Length: 112
RNA sequence: AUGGCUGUCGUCAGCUCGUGUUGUGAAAUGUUGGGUUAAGUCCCGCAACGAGCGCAACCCUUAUCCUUUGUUGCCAGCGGU
Ligand SMILES: [Mg+2]
Ligand SMILES: [Mg+2]
Ligand SMILES: [Mg+2]
Ligand SMILES: [Mg+2]
Ligand SMILES: [Mg+2]
Ligand SMILES: [Mg+2]
Ligand SMILES: [Mg+2]
Ligand SMILES: [Mg+2]
Image: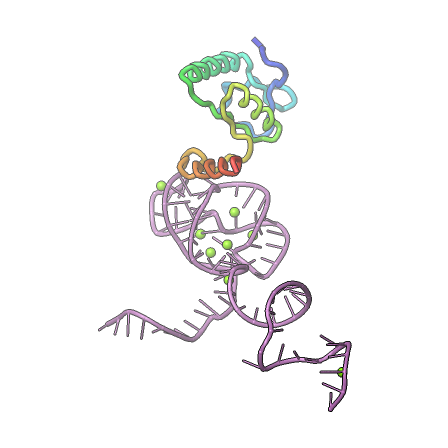
């Protein structure tokens, strides 16, 4: 059921064809998602995230679009996980060996 | 055939590498873009993240002042010559 609040979908422009099964679609030439399809998927995702946390893992929230910036740092501060709040540095994971020095370099400033 | 040394483009601001990513590949990106600088100088942005040789600084000299020392250098204030 509609556990959600009020979003009823968005993104009138440039709709991706391969998302047709998730589209309900109607008003004011703006697509609206099929929340009936969403709820089982969101619950399934929520259940899985838990399993991971239960084996002790990090989730690394990612959301860099202004609006959500503060929303992310807070949600990630709580739950003691980690987050990326601003521009995602290309290669932040593929070459972790190089960004590691930047972290170590950063740690130096805080201590000094 | 060479070492060493030297001129020259040019004291011009450029030249590259590690990892990552893109391309079948030669390669590309970074190093491009908006401003700015004498400067690849700096800031912002950005599949790039960092680094090196260059630029700048550290060197010599010149322009002001202070402390120390005062002869073979100096003579403001004192004595007569
Ligand atoms: Mg390849
Ligand atoms: Mg170049
Ligand atoms: Mg290039
Ligand atoms: Mg530029
Ligand atoms: Mg430079
Ligand atoms: Mg750049
Ligand atoms: Mg120099
Ligand atoms: Mg006299």
